[PDB]
Length: 5
Length: 231
Image (cartoon, rainbow over all chains, first blue to last red; front, side):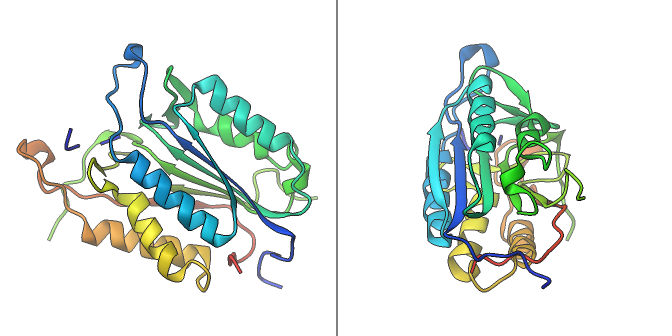
């Protein structure tokens, strides 16, 4: 959730 | 004399590829926050004077076909061209919803020998995607490849951070700087200020110490031969 690509 | 000619009917076309949802076979989660990014981008680039079209959840074949057709259009009355890629990524490669495709294969369609109507005109590519798996811990006749510019969200090998609630760092910084100075600054000044903003204003927060207090620095690759203003 709360993270990158 | 040292600037790109902006004396055309239209500024140009801006293609925004917003990949949020991905096939299960790719094993990648939903890119929450990318819609905020895409909308902000659409407004900023519309404000600059672009004719912006947003495509969502595209496949590799779809992205290739898109940029192909765009390369085959008539940009005679266009000052420039712009493409934005919002997706998952690895080094030299970007994700469609089906899988992966090489970025160079996306941008090659607009090469001088392939897109004659954009000859001597700037081709801009903004890529919000990861370029590897490494982390920043921080500390306290004319060439066919000419007139290209790539604005990557991060340096090769490193991650590109994205806040599900606020959007990705690079895109939101870029959008702010474009809101304020998009028309009175040269493109490299803008992207430099974007570098500064992303570098300083951001520090990741996570319960996993592996992703706690981490940093990011964007990357600009310029093959431009003139200065670029959007006015």
